Image (cartoon, rainbow, N blue to C red):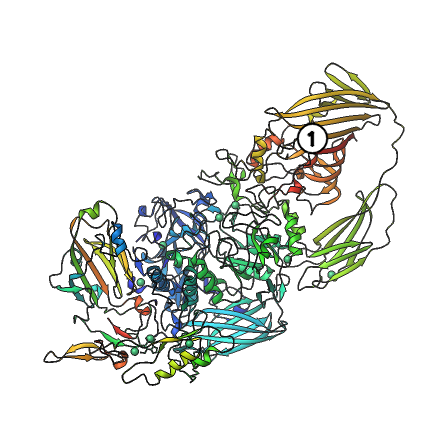
Amino acid sequence: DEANIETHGMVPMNRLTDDPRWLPAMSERVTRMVQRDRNHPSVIIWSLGNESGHGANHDALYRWIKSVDPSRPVQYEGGGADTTATDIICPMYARVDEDQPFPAVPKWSIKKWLSLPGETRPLILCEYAHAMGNSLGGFAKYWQAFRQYPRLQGGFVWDWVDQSLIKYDENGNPWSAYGGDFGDTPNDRQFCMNGLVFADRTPH
Amino acid sequence: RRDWENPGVTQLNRLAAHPPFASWRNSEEARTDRPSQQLRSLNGEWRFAWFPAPEAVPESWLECDLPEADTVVVPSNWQMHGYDAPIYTNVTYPITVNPPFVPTENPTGCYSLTFNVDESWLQEGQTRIIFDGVNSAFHLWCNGRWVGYGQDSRLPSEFDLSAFLRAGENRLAVMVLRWSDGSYLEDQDMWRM
Amino acid sequence: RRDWENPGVTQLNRLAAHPPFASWRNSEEARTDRPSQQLRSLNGEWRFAWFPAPEAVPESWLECDLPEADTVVVPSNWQMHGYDAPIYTNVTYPITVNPPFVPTENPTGCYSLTFNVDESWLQEGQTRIIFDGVNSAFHLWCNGRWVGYGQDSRLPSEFDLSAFLRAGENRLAVMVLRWSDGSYLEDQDMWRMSGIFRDVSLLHKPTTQISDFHVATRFNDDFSRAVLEAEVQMCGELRDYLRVTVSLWQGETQVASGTAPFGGEIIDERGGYADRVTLRLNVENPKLWSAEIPNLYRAVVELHTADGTLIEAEACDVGFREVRIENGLLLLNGKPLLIRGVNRHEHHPLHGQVMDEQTMVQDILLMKQNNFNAVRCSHYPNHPLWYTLCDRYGLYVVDEANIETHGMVPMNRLTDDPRWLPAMSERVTRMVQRDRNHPSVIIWSLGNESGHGANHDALYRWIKSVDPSRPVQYEGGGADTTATDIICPMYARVDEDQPFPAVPKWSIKKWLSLPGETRPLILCEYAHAMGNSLGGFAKYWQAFRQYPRLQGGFVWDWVDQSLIKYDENGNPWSAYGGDFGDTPNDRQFCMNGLVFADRTPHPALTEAKHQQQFFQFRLSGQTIEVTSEYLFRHSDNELLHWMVALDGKPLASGEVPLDVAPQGKQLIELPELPQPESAGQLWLTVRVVQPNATAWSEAGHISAWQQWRLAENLSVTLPAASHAIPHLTTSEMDFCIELGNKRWQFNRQSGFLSQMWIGDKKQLLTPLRDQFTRAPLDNDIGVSEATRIDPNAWVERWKAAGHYQAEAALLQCTADTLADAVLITTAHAWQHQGKTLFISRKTYRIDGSGQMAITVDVEVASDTPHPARIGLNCQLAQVAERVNWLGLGPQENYPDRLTAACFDRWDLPLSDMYTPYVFPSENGLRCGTRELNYGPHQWRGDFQFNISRYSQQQLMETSHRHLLHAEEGTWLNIDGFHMGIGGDDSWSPSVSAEFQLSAGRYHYQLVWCQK
Ligand SMILES: OC[C@@H]1[C@H](O)[C@H](O)[C@@H](O)c2nnnn21
Ligand SMILES: OC[C@@H]1[C@H](O)[C@H](O)[C@@H](O)c2nnnn21
Ligand SMILES: [Mg+2]
Ligand SMILES: [Mg+2]
Ligand SMILES: [Mg+2]
Ligand SMILES: [Mg+2]
Ligand SMILES: [Mg+2]
Ligand code: NA
Ligand code: NA
Ligand code: NA
Ligand code: NA
Ligand code: NA
C-alpha cells in the first residue's frame, strides 16, 4: 500500500520532500492511508510514495509508521533504493548481473547489491521487467536469480495494463489512443502503455 | 483565501480518517458483511458544469441549479465526458513548476445534487458525507452554506452535514479544481485527469 | 475563518525560518558583529487598546488609531500594564479543555504603530517585519491591508511587507489573541500572560540574498585537525557570476577562506541544488570550544559578484566541538561530561516574560560563579540573545521545542494524534532551523510533559536526520522511550525506587543497569528548590562522581516566578499564584528557584556551588591531594589557601600555587604544624582562589573549599574553687534560685523555667519549653490543601497526630541542694487524644560559677510520626544587634543541607539569621554549633539553632513574607536534633531515612550562662 506522494518533476527530486514546510501535507498522505487501511490482512508492506528523492520528511514518516504499526515492514525506493527510510532494498530496474553505477543513485546488479559491505536487508524489486510493447526479453534471468539467492525475494513487474484510452473515428470506430492524441501538449507519447495486458484486458 | 495555493492548508472542516464503517444497527448483518441501512450511496446522476477558472463561477450556482448544466453520471472524470482534455505527461509537470502556485486558468467542475434525507437521520446522531475520490481539491456547500474543503485525490474526505441538512429535499454544491498545491504531490506517470 | 481555532492553520503568509540574519552590506561589520543599517528595531512606544473578544474590534482600528488607546512600551505583556490579570496555573489548563476551541470571551490586544519608512528601502530589495515573540496568536495588517497570521509564542514569525509599505508614514495593526489552538501546546507550569513580548524589528535584504546557511565542524581522532563545512542557500535570480565566499577568523587573524559559484553535488536522478553551495575549510590544531574555555571563531558568509562586488553578508560565532554518545557515555571533544546544570525560565519580577540583556548577563554570571556549567531552556526556545551569550561565556545548552500539553488526559492525548503532527512539527523544525549554528546548544529536546506519542518518534527522527551532530532527548512516557538518546528523568531519587505504574521513576543507580539498558543518564529536572529545600543535594553529587554513566542533571530551578505587587503605601511585595484574582491557581508552586526573583541568592545556592566543585581534595598526614575534575584546562587561574584554627582561633595558614592538569592530581605537603597550648579541636580549611578576574568573575573569586578535623585535645582540666553557693527558695508555687545578681524561677505546677533575671531585668517573654514541631516547609506541606488534604504529607501526619496541639502535662518537679549546686529535676508528657506522644525528662544544675547545666532526655513513642524537631524554645526579652557563634555557617544550614557550611567562628547582624522566603516557614537554622552568643547570653553544647523576631507560630500562620511583623523580643529555637528538610521533590515526603528522628531515645545537654 503506497502513499499518494510523487514529486518526480522537481529539481532536484527531493526538493519538496526535504522541505519542512511540506511535511504536513506529506504526512496526511501517509497517516491517512495507514489509518484507513491498517486492518486489511492483504496489506503486507507500506510504501512512502514514489520518485520524490529522499528527504528528511521521508525518515520522519518512516518512523511514524514503524512506530504506530510495527506489524508491517516499510519500504521506499527514492534516493537510491537502500536509504535509512527502507526496511527492504527495493530498486527499480536493477539488472541481474549488470551494474549501472549512476552517480549518487547507482543501480547495482541485484546479486551484487545484497552483499555490499555492511548490507544485510532482503531485496525485492519495486519495479522490474518493463513490459512496454514487444518486451520481457531476459525475464527468465531474474527468476533464475530469485530462486538461487535466498535474500533475492522477487519483484513487481512494470506493469499490469496499458494506459491506452478509447477515441472514435468518423464511423464511430473506436481505436486505442496514447499521449498527444487529445491534443495534449507536452506529452509522453506511447510511454503510458507498458502493460502485460492490453487496456481491454486481452493478454499480451 | 485561495486555499488551493497553500500546502499549509490541505483541508477544512474534514473529519478524521478511520477504517471502513457502515454503522450496522443489526449485528448479524455486520457479521455477514451485508448492506447497511445507515450507509447510502449518492452515486448516479448529478448536475455538472465546467468553468475555466474558479473566478468564473456564478454565486447563483450555490443557491440554484445552473440551467446550462448537463446531467452526468458520478463518479466519473470530466475529461472522459469531453469537457476538456486528459494530458499524458510522464515526468514533466502539466503545469508550470512554481510551488505552491497553480495556473490562473484552472479548469473548475461544478457538480451538484438534489437528494433526500429522511427525518430519522436528522432526529438523532450524525450524518456525514463521504467522497472517496476528488481530484485534485474541492470546496463543498450544502443548501447554499459552505461546509469545508479537501485535498489528496486518492483518499476519502469526510464532512459532517448534520447541521446543514433538512428532512426532505436537499442541495449539495461541489466546486472541484483541476490543479492545486496538492498537484505538486501528484506527479505520477499517467494521464492527468 | 477563526484561524485561531484550527491546528491545521498555524500561520498565513509567514516566511520560512532561518538562522539570525542582519543583512550587512559591509564584510567587516559582519565579522565584528556590529550593528547593521539594514536591521531596525521598532521597539518602544506603540498604541494599545484591550478587548474582551476579537469580535468587538472596531473594524475602524484597521485604518485609524483609536483614541481610547493608550501609549505603552513594547515588548511587553499586557497583564504587566494592568489591562488584565496574569494567571498562575501549573497543570490545569487555564481554559476549558475542548481542543481546538478556545473561550468566546478571549482577551484581545490591539497594537498599532505609526512609523516612517525610507523609500530607499522600497525602491529595491525586500522589507520584512519580524516579531520575535507574540503570545499566543495574531493577525497582521499594514496600511489597512491584511498581511498574515502566526502561532507559537516562542519563535520568531516574519512577513514580507515589501508590497504593503509606502514612502513615509505608515500604520501597522496587530491583533493579538490571548488564546488560540496554540495554547494547547503551551501548558507550561508558569504564569499565563500575553502580548508582543519579544522584539519587533524590520530587516532589509537584497532580492538576490542568502536565505539560510549551516555550519558543521568534524574532527580527526585526536581533535588535532578539523574540517569546517558550510552549506549556503540563496533566493533571487541565479546568475553565473554569483559567488559565495566563506571565510573563518580567530579574531583579527583570517584562518581560512574559500570561494565557489552556486551548484551543489548531484543528489538524485533529478540532479542537484542549483541554488546552494557547500564550502569546506581545513583547520589545523583548532582551538576547541567547551564551557571550560569558550574558544570561538568568526564565520563570515559573503554573497558576491565575480567582479568582487558584495551583495550582502551574514555571519555567526563558531565553536569547534564534537558531541557524541559512545559506549553509553556522553562525550564532548572525546571526553565524558559531568553536567552541573540548572533549568531556567525567562522571568522578570516587574517585566513578566519580557527579557533584557542585563538580566540575562546577570543570570549567567551568577550561574558560572556558582559552578554551573549548563542550562536547559524549560520549556521553549529562548529569546535569541541567550544563545549568543551562552556561546561566549560558555554554558552547555539544552534547546527545547515549545510543546507542553501536561493538562491533557492522558498526557499524550494530542501528541499521539496525527492531526496534531503538523503544528507540533513546526514547533520543532523552526527551533532547529533558527538555532542549529550555535555551539552552546549541545542537545535538542522535543518538549515537556506531553506523554509519549507517535508524533514524538517522528520528530525525533526528523532531527537525527537533519542534524546528526547533537543528541536528541525527551523525558515524557517514562524518560527512557524510543524517542530519547539519554535517560533523562525528572526527580528520580538516588537510591530510592518510586515504581509508579507505567512510568516508574527507578533509583538512578538502578535505572542504568536494567536489563538491556545502555544509555547515559542525565536528569532533566532534579533537587526541586522550593523554599527551604535542597536537602540531600550531596547524595546526588556523590553518585554522579562514583558512576561513569550518571552524568549530572539540571536542578529545578534557577529563579522564583514571583511578580511584584504594591500595597496601599505603594510598597512592593512579591506575589504569587492567586494574588491577581486569578483562579483557579497553584499558589506558591511557581516559586522553586535557587535565587529570589530579584536575583538575590537563596541559601541553597551555596550548597549547589560546593557540591559542583571542579577540584576534589583528599587529606592524609600532612598531605593534601587535589584532583581536578576539569576535562580540558589546567588550573591556570588558581591558587590554594590553607588555614589551621583551634576552635576558631587561627593558628597557621599559607598558600601554594596549584598546577593541575585536567583529571590530574597534585600533592601539597604541609609544613610541620605546631601543637597547641590547650584543649580543643583543630580544623584545617582549604579554599581555591582565582587570582585574576575573568569574563564572569572578579579577582579573588573562591571556587572551592573543604574542611577536616585534625588532632583534638579533650579538656581534662578540672574547673575551680567554686567562689559562692546558689541558694534555693522553695515556695508552694516556685523553686527559686539565687546567686549574686542572678535569679532563676521554676514554676512548680508548670515544671518549666518561667523567669530568669540579671540585675532587676527579666530575661524571658515566655517560659523555656521543649518544642517538637516546625512551621511547615514547602516540602513538609507538599500538595496538601485545606480543601483537599494530602494525608501523606509530613505536615498532615504531624497535625493529625496532634503534634501541633500536644499539651505538656507535668509528671514531676523536684529541687534538691548539692554540695555546691542546686539541682531541679522535671518530667513531662505530651499527650494527644489520650496517647503519650513524648516524654521529656530534664535536670537543671546551677553551680556557684553561675552556669546553668541542662540535661534533656526525650522519649518518642514508636508509633507516632517522627517529629520535626527535638529541642527547647523561649522568647527572650532582649533584642540585640548581633549573633555570634562557633559552629557551622555562615548561612542557614540543615542536617541534609550542611556540606557547604564551614565550622568556625561566625558573626552577623540579627537579620542575617532569618531567611526571607516568600512563603514563610521554619528557617535560618545553623547546625553543629558548640557555642552560641546573644546579648549577655551564652549557650554551649552540641546543637542546632535559629534566632529571629518571628515565633514559629506566626510563621506557620503567615503566607506572605510581607505580612510578617517583628514580635516583641527575640525568638530562640535551640535543638538537640532537627529533621532533615528534603527536596528530591516537593510533592511527597522526600526526607531520607537517616535524616528522620526515629531513634526513639534522644539525649542532649546544654550550658547556659552569662557574659
Ligand atoms: O513506465 C516507466 C515507469 C513509471 O514511470 C513508474 O511510475 C516510475 O516509477 C518509473 N521509474 N522508471 N520507470 N518508471
Ligand atoms: O515546579 C514543578 C516542576 C515544573 O512543573 C516543571 O515545569 C515540570 O517539568 C515539572 N514536573 N514535575 N515538577 N515539575
Ligand atoms: Mg492547500
Ligand atoms: Mg515518475
Ligand atoms: Mg490555528
Ligand atoms: Mg507541567
Ligand atoms: Mg594556578
Ligand atoms: Na530468493
Ligand atoms: Na510509463
Ligand atoms: Na558520573
Ligand atoms: Na513550579
Ligand atoms: Na508558612
Q: Residue at point 22% right, 79% down?
A: A178
Answer left or right for B67 relative to C712. left
Query: Is there any visible trace of residue A149 in the rendered image?
Result: yes
Determine the secondary structure under disc 1: strand
Residue A131 % position (x, y): 30, 81
Of residues C398 and C166, which is closer to you in this image?
Answer: C398
Q: Chain of mark 1?
A: C
Answer left or right for C471 relative to A67. right
Residue C333 % position (x, y): 61, 67
Farthest residue toward the right?
A: C721
Q: Residue at point 49% right, 41% down?
A: C586
Answer left or right for C873 relative to C19. right
**Residue B140: which quarter of the image?**
bottom left
Query: Is there any visible trace of residue C239 in the rendered image?
Result: no
Answer left or right for C723 relative to C403. right
Asked if ligand 12 lies within 8 A of label 1, the reply is no
Farthest residue toward the top?
A: C732
Decide: is A191 above or below C320: below
Q: If the image is split into quadrants, where does the N terminus of chain C sit?
A: bottom left
Quick check: which quadrant has ligand 10? bottom right
Q: Residue at point 33% right, 62% down?
A: A40
Of residues A131 and C551, which is closer to you in this image?
Answer: A131
**Residue C958: which quarter of the image?**
top right
Of residues C992 and B32, which is closer to you in this image?
Answer: B32
Residue A135 % position (x, y): 30, 84
Residue B53 % position (x, y): 21, 66
Q: Residues within 10 Å of mark 1 (few under 14, many from 20)?
A: some
Q: Amino acid at mark 1?
A: Glu
Of residues A126 and C317, which is closer to you in this image?
Answer: A126
Q: If the image is split into quadrants, where does the C terminus of chain C sit?
A: top right
Residue ID for mark 1: C859
